[PDB]
Image 1 (cartoon, rainbow over the protein chains, first blue to last red):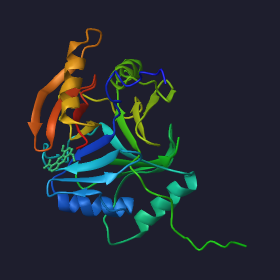
Image 2: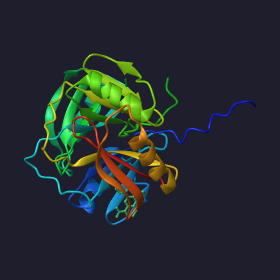
Image 3: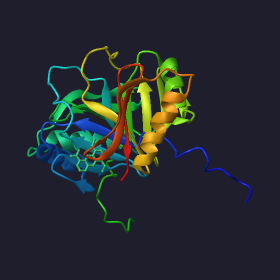
Image 4: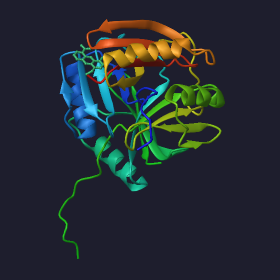
Length: 132
Length: 132
Ligand SMILES: COc1ccc(C=O)c2nc3cccc(C(=O)O)c3nc12
């Protein structure tokens, strides 16, 4: 070709979503349950789960320990194909008994569509909604 | 009738990384600059950028406004092909003259290799680190 397209560095993508956890074992168990998936990389302080493409979601005990009382300003979002899927997942999580699932917001409509919020063991906010 | 017996729900993936922002237009400009990409969609309150694959990174003014000095317990991560790419990006971002970038931590080798930290306009932590 005549196409010198690789002279400006690698692409810059927010391909990691990382949350600080108090205990990696407990959070690994929690996210295995939420995602119905095994992690792709496991170490005692850092565990990664797949996202789309080359992106990852990771839990890490090397940051600052989360404090329950402190308000949070970001969310771990899970986009499902349809609004029916959102309601089915809410029903599944709130009916099953083994795993504690803390509901923060009941299903409602927001900018995302039909959506609900739960908390993880360290107070991280998880949103379920439809695909864009 | 149906010839399918699969009763599984849809794949559950953390495919939305969402942060709360005070000034959507300001944050749109910031992220357009650091990602060198246009948003997928823009509304007054809600803007998304591509992450990898089908995943998105989004900014939203409809949550709770982030407050300076409230500690944060999560990071927006940017994973690059090599450690050398990490140092090169820090040089690029600190050399350019057109956008203020607040540096939290200059480059160094952590337990996972070369890394640095910056802040976004609303105090969200952004980490640059290596894939490998
Ligand atoms: C923020 O933390 C990380 C980011 C990206 C990584 C790339 O795979 C990564 N890998 C690790 C491998 C071993 C141990 C740790 C640890 O932090 O103890 C790791 N932490 C990592």
